[PDB]
Length: 265
Ligand SMILES: Cc1cc(CNc2nccc(Nc3cc(CCc4ccccc4)[nH]n3)n2)on1
Image (cartoon, rainbow, N blue to C red; front, side):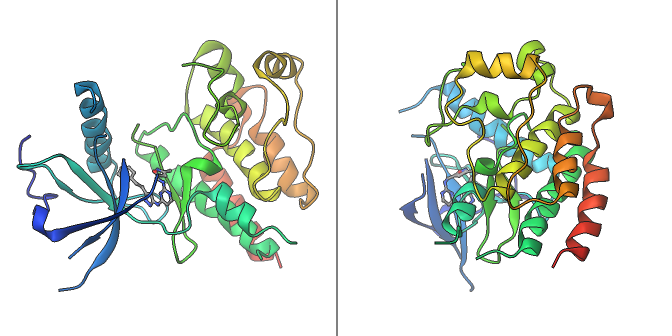
């Protein structure tokens, strides 16, 4: 694999450590920085294709506070190691669930939403469409900064590691017509807001795929969470507009969340 001196880190500068979920925690060196490293598990060439793709797409997208940023790579004379920012508190779902009462203020929760919307606006400005935006693909740093993940990356019945179905984040036009746009991502954003305000709640509990389809076709919409203002619930519903052109954009969402954060206790 060809050397990219913008990014290449010598192998002897990386101290591999504990597994994270093939993603390990590591130390890049006179000061050490904790980072996350991805590597290939016996794997296909495709798997190597996919890995390199993820890395190159990160090269192009650029730096933002609210996304997992590439930090380097080990490409010469060994397996490929992609090195990125480490977020010590795991995904947004786990972070949220672990701070359920028997803590996060109202303002904290709104602040999370604002940050994810910021990350998404940037990715959008860079022409990137996520296709699986969800609390589980948002990671949280030690400083509680939201960072979007898996933006550089179907069986509708495959469940996640935690027993939930991804189709439940998917806008209708993407689900039935496989048409994906920034506006389908905005739909998924609306679902992710629901997760924030139900402190890591699971959407449509007990609803399998086929019944899911029935609900969407009938125009069903999730109930308002208990820890939710009408304004924030309207924001969700606007995200779930039947007609994609009539959904807000992440630009709009960022501006509205900025104002709300400010006025939230
Ligand atoms: C999303 C996601 C989660 C993981 C690995 N699981 C995990 N568990 C706990 C903490 C944690 N921290 C991480 C993970 C990362 C991104 C790793 C990465 C992604 C793409 C390319 C190279 C490395 N940062 N902090 N991760 O993976 N994804």
